[PDB]
Length: 282
Ligand SMILES: [Cl-]
Ligand SMILES: [Cl-]
Image 1 (tube, rainbow, N blue to C red):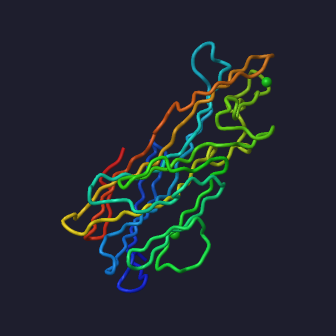
Image 2: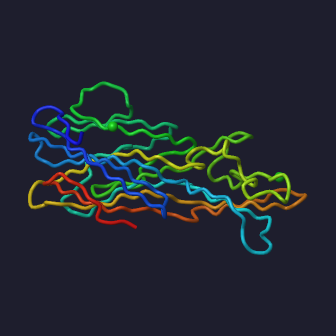
Image 3: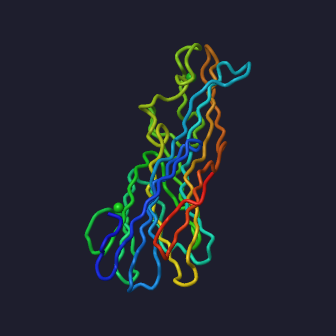
């Protein structure tokens, strides 16, 4: 189940890697599909990036005197998915999502026909008019997807915090009092200073399950192997909630406190032997 006939003297060699990190709280479940097609004089690798990026959300006390009633909530303001390469021989010919998509569910399809013909569709609908297709699918309740950077050598997506449903209407990702609440007593736990799990969406509470694609073209001839990095990470904001007994709760946001905390894995493609292997990581 690692080689598939897609029509003609054309087939797809399916390879997959699974690299994880407890430090970064990330898991890369990538699928590297090589496109073998005599009628298309260029190597092509369809990389489908999946896995899990831990929200890394944490509620805790704040050490130091004068802060006994100041609690801290750390959460992911944005998830980061990206793939960059340096080898001159390689170029990114396509990527999904191609444009900014802000619906709760993201479902797109990358199609391929013999003769090097790729086309994308922002829907997982019909209708098998491709020799081979790969699809992305992920939910982002309260978040928005956008292509931060892109060129022939790299692509980088960002799943940003956008708007959240609250007991009292909507609230933006920049609202300083987002997720804060009085804990019903000064003896209340750190967690009680913030919104309960039922009001927190998956991307905040649990984490994010990425699902992205990007095809790489390669010039046949003394360009035997290429390397590229894949980043899965997040940008974290801090939300401090201080209880003034008998008064109320004072909150303050520290936006972009921990940016670019990413887990970068370096891979190598052996175009000739149609094979993949991990060179290293952080
Ligand atoms: Cl698929
Ligand atoms: Cl209050």
